[PDB]
Length: 18
Image (cartoon, rainbow, N blue to C red):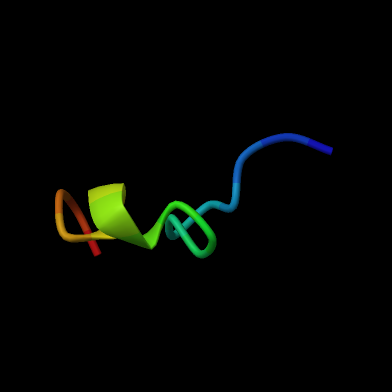
């Protein structure tokens, strides 16, 4: 529906802010 918010599946980018 949009973004994973915390970078869930996007966990490689997750470390940017989460």
